[PDB]
Image (cartoon, rainbow, N blue to C red):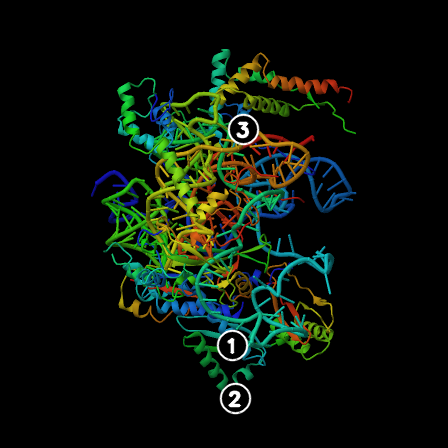
RNA sequence: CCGGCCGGGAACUCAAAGGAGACUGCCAGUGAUAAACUGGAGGAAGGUGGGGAUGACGUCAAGUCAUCAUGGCCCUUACGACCAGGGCUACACACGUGCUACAAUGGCGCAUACAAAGAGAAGCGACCUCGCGAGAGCAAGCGGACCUCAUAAAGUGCGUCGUAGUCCGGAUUGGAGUCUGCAACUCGACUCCAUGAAGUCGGAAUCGCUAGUAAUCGUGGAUCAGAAUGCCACGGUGAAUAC
């Protein structure tokens, strides 16, 4: 087990943080756990909506949750009853007056959360993994994407030993720190157990 | 007289915010000293990186809190009216204590 | 030393006599990074050496150290090889200091003042170390 | 008039002020033999002033803080050689040649994880 | 040792000792409370102290008083 | 020099030759020489006889040699006759004050047997 | 880590701020140089889990007792996971 | 009021943001006129300047089902749950890693100088009074370049000790206590008085370190009500040697 998380080593360099509140030591743990609850809830209740990121920020006793998603229409719905329902329950969880926004992730096959969730969904619909991976690499390289690597792992095809079998195309410069590597990871709970899907997407060199 | 002490985790974000509060204040009121920087607090955390034995593999982390101090001298009513409700900062803690 | 041929770092000379030779002698004597203590011992011991022998300071030191410098040093062969000058007086000082730590007098300045005085008429312990090295390289002269 | 040098050495900082005058040295409102001149190597604050001599040449008011004994002393040496812009760049030929204008940038190496100190690795058993 | 202010006994052991000296020393006492400093009124009683598995009877002599109960009930059996 | 018993110390500073008395260390010895009005660094040679029995008169006010040895012995016997933890522990010859006997109980337990 | 233990932890906190910080008053004020009666030393028949020295500070997410970090409120494992994803603001790798 | 103490000054240290800087860039020589190497100047730094982060494809069916998640199996009036007491601290032994030593380059007493990095509200807790001391009482200031922790210690200058198991060493043990905590018996930490082992430089063997390094000296922090000789950091002094 030996590679650094390629989001974490780029946190001040190119990648931003998904939480951008300041807090002193008295409420740092409380704000942090409140963020675990709103991302847990808001991740479970938008499983069909293809959600990429949820960014929390707290401007002066009020949360401001931004849902980067690929299907904004299914998040908002017929006149946005679903949004006001979500800020009602996020205001229930965080205990502050909640705002909520939706940012449309166009080009959803270049986002690693959406790619890993895609391949994970296909693996738990019992399709063969080489199609899922290989289709994901092809259609991601089709639109921009100066590199992509996907990597499934663990008891693939229902075996009794676990393999990995990664694929990559293009250039994925993972030790370069100015590389805009969009990396994310999902787990596929199949009837044989968990299958881990990692995906790195190299977008640009700065 | 009116010290506004700003704290944030991102130095670009805090010097943007304090540049805005400086030009706001000395644009409306008068006699702003300047964004004095006041040492960054580096809090370091050294966690074990493995879920079992393996002490020697550890990951070191830090949170850098940046301060800035402004210290606006003239107590104009225009600068305290115009100084309130105008921040547009998200990760800044201000202290506007007189 | 596998690849890297090296330079060497320059030591500051002695603050009383300007002698880098004696500065390396207080570094050979120093233990636990305590240099003040070691230079106190060297100033006291060489001061009583200059008072006893009546010559001067560092020519009494240079004579007492001139009597302990090795000439040459040593299948398993023990070949004799010619000592470089920096290594020559480095070994001289290491043997003086080590033999002075072996002695049974009161203070370190007396152990080392008596060891340098015993090396001035070359009858001490460091001269027995030099004669021992020279018996090893003299017995095994047959390898060059 | 008044001639300045910044002069730092392993966590020290020696402000060195020079006026022309006698051969006195005033360090933190204290003489040289009373600041650290009861201790090891007060010669090194006097080494820049033996390249051309200080006999009755210049009074220097110096103010050092941070560091230890030797750190402060090396800081004053670097401070005086930075403060010998009193005479022109003449001195800084020979003063360069003694190795005095070099900021000695040896600092204490940090302690690293799994090592007791900066490089002393803890001892390892059988094999 | 401990405690500039008061010694320690449990209140249930206080009440069992008061009733034990009032109505006479009839039976050994089930005490789990090893935390408890022997008082001078407890002299002559047989207080069984729990050692993890067994209540072992402790007859209180006069010189038990500056001591905890559990000193007289060893917990580990070494042979 | 025969103070507090058969103890005869001599040719040594008075703060330190008094430490030969079983039951006076450095503190109690400073207390004896301060209470008897004696300088701390005089020897017993170069010290008068009236001065010596002022030291006897001062050392008599603390529990020393015989009374202290039988007081200590009495304390240990009380513990071992109680059969408390400190007495069973004191009796078997194993460390009393809650120390480690898995290894490194070796003053109390003596040099290792097989 | 064993649901029971997390429930046990919530019990101890709830008793800790019911009784004590209100009747821990006793141990701060009456056990003192004032008079005395033995009474308030015996008025520690409070349910023993009102004592705040019986909270463990488990991880907020997994209830792990060891490796806790009071700043973040999490064990070292969830601190690293969340730190790398970017949910802990300001926190990044350190090197000096 | 001799203290940056005040008015004041923004030079300087410094603080933190933004830039400049080091690239074989220049020179000489050697080299396929190539890569480059060796040496020189300038420069704070010279050749990946120092240190860190960064750990390729894979190996060990290496470690973790006890952080978590999880397939299957298994218990489901019990292998689940609540409680008190105990244990994880046991001790003929053996091994690992450390601390303290065996001393005079030192021990002790008196005076006196020079740090860096940190932490702090159910917290850090001055001053002053009491206690030999650990501490106690009243209690300012500080959510903190402002206050507190907090005196750096080795160093230096005097005096003493005088090669003794000693003024070394502090284990062990008795007594008396302080604090935290419902509660120090099993089973804390610290203090005071007393005790004063083993140990005089370590067999075979073995380990770390290439320069602010080893060695040695202190300080801080996390966990934590209280409990470090460990861990993670910080600075002080500061080597030897590399054919």
The crowd level at tag 2 (other Cα within 10 Å; few <14, some 14-19, many 20+) is: few
User: SS for tag 2?
Assistant: loop
Q: What percent of the width, then of the height, locates residue H75? A: 61, 74
Q: Is residue D61 visible?
A: no
Nearer to us: label 3 or label 1: 1
Q: Which residue is the site of mark 2?
A: A78
| Camera-nearest residue between D61 and H218 | H218
| Camera-nearest residue between H211 and E25 | E25
Place residue G10 in its image quadrant: bottom left
User: SS for tag 1?
Assistant: helix
Q: Which residue is the site of mark 1?
A: A41
Tell me if E13 is positioned left or right of B1 in this view.
right
Q: Are marks 3 and 1 in contact (CB under 8 Å)?
A: no
Q: What percent of the width, then of the height, locates residue A156? A: 72, 71
Measure how far apart labels 3 and 1 are at the Cα level: 69 Å
> What residue is drawn where x is 52% and y is 88%?
A78
Q: What percent of the width, then of the height, locates residue G2? A: 53, 68
Asked if badges 2 and 3 are on one and the same chain, I answer: no
Asked if badges 1 and 2 are on one and the same chain, I answer: yes
Nearer to us: label 1 or label 2: 1
> What residue is drawn where x is 62% and y is 44%?
D124
Measure how far apart labels 2 and 3 are at the Cα level: 85 Å
Q: Is residue C75 visible?
A: yes
Does G75 appear above or below A108?
above
Q: Chain of mark 2?
A: A
Asked if badges 3 and 1 are on one and the same chain, I answer: no
**Which label sits on residue C27?**
3
Measure how far apart labels 1 and 2 are at the Cα level: 22 Å
**Which label sits on residue D99?**
none
- Quadrant holding the N terminus of chain B: bottom left
- Quadrant holding the C terminus of chain B: bottom left
């Amino acid at each position: 087990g030996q590679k650094v998380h390629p989001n974490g080593i780029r946190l001040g360099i190119v990648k931003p943080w998904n939480s951008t509140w300041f807090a002193n030591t008295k409420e740092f743990a409380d704000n942090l756990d409140s963020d675990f609850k709103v991302r847990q809830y808001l991740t479970k209740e938008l499983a069909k909506a293809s959600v990429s990121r949820i960014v929390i920020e707290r401007p002066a006793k009020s949360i401001r949750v931004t849902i980067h998603t690929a299907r904004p229409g299914i998040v908002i719905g017929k006149k946005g009853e679903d949004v006001e329902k979500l800020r009602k329950v996020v205001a229930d969880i965080a205990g502050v007056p909640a705002q909520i926004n939706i940012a449309e992730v166009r080009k959803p096959e270049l986002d690693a959360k959406l790619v890993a969730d895609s391949i994970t969904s296909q693996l738990e619909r019992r399709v063969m993994f080489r199609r899922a991976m290989k289709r994901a690499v092809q259609n991601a390289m089709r639109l921009g994407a100066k590199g992509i690597k996907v990597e499934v792992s663990g008891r693939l095809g229902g075996a009794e030993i676990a393999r990995t079998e990664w694929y990559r195309e293009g250039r994925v410069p993972l030790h370069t720190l100015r590389a805009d590597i969009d990396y994310n990871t999902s787990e596929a709970h199949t009837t044989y157990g968990v299958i881990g899907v990692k995906v790195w997407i190299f977008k640009g060199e700065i | 007289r009116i010290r506004i002490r700003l704290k944030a985790f991102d130095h670009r974000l805090i010097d943007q915010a304090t540049a805005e509060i400086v030009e706001t204040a000395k644009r409306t009121g008068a006699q702003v000293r300047g964004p004095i920087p006041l040492p960054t607090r580096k809090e370091r955390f050294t966690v074990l990186i493995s879920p079992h034995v393996n002490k020697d593999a550890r990951d070191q982390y830090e949170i850098r809190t940046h301060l800035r101090l402004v210290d606006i001298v003239e107590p104009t009513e225009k600068t305290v009216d115009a100084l309130m409700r105008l921040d547009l900062a998200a990760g800044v803690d201000v202290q506007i204590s007189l | 030393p596998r690849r890297r041929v090296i330079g060497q770092r320059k030591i500051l000379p002695d603050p009383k006599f300007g002698s880098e030779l004696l500065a390396k002698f207080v570094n050979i004597l120093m233990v636990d990074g305590k240099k003040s203590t070691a230079e106190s011992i060297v100033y006291s011991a060489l001061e009583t050496l200059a008072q006893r022998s009546g010559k001067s300071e560092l020519e009494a030191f240079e004579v007492a150290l001139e009597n302990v410098r090795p000439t040459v040093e040593v299948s398993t062969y023990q070949v004799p090889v010619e000592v470089r000058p920096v290594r020559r007086n480095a070994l001289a000082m290491r043997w003086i200091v080590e033999a002075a730590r072996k002695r049974g007098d009161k203070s370190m300045a007396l152990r080392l003042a008596n060891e340098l005085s015993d090396a001035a008429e070359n009858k001490g312990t460091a001269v027995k170390k030099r004669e021992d090295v020279h018996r090893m390289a003299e017995a095994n002269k047959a390898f060059a | 008039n008044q001639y300045y040098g910044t002069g730092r050495r392993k966590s020290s900082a020696a402000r060195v002020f020079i006026k022309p005058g006698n051969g006195k040295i005033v360090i933190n409102q204290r003489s040289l033999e009373q600041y650290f001149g009861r201790e090891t190597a007060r010669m090194v604050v006097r080494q820049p002033l033996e390249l051309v001599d200080m006999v009755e040449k210049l009074d220097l008011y110096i103010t050092v803080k941070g560091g230890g004994i030797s750190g402060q002393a090396g800081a004053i040496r670097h401070g005086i050689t930075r403060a010998l812009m009193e005479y022109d760049e003449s001195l800084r030929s020979e003063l360069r040649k003694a190795g005095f204008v070099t900021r000695d940038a040896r600092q204490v190496e940090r302690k690293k994880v799994g090592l007791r100190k900066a490089r002393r690795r803890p001892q390892f058993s059988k094999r | 040792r401990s405690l500039k202010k008061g010694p320690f006994i449990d209140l249930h052991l206080l009440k069992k000792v008061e009733k034990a000296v009032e109505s006479g020393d009839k039976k050994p006492l089930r005490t789990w409370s090893r935390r408890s400093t022997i008082f001078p009124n407890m002299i002559g009683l047989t207080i069984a102290v729990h050692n993890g598995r067994q209540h072992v009877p402790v007859f209180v002599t006069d010189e038990m008083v500056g001591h905890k109960l559990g000193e007289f009930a060893p917990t580990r059996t070494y042979r | 020099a025969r103070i507090a018993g058969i103890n005869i110390p001599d040719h040594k500073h008075a703060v330190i030759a008094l430490t030969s008395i079983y039951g006076v260390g450095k503190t109690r010895s400073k207390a004896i020489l301060a209470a008897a009005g004696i300088a701390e660094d005089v020897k017993i040679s170069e010290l008068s006889e009236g001065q010596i029995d002022t030291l006897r008169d001062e050392v008599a006010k603390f529990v020393v040699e015989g009374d202290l040895r039988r007081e200590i012995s009495m304390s240990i016997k009380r513990l071992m006759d109680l059969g408390c933890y400190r007495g069973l522990r004191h009796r078997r010859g194993l460390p009393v004050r809650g120390q480690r006997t898995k290894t490194n109980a070796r003053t109390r337990k003596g040099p290792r047997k097989p | 880590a064993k649901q029971s233990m997390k429930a046990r932890e919530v019990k101890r906190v709830a008793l800790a701020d019911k009784y004590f910080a209100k009747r821990a008053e006793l141990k701060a004020i009456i056990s003192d140089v004032n008079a005395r009666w033995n009474a308030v030393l015996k008025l520690q028949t409070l349910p023993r889990d009102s004592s705040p020295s019986r909270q463990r500070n488990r991880c907020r997410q997994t209830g792990r007792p060891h490796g806790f970090l009071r700043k973040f409120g999490l064990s070292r494992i969830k601190v690293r996971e969340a730190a790398m994803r970017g949910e802990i603001p300001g926190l990044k790798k350190a090197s000096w």
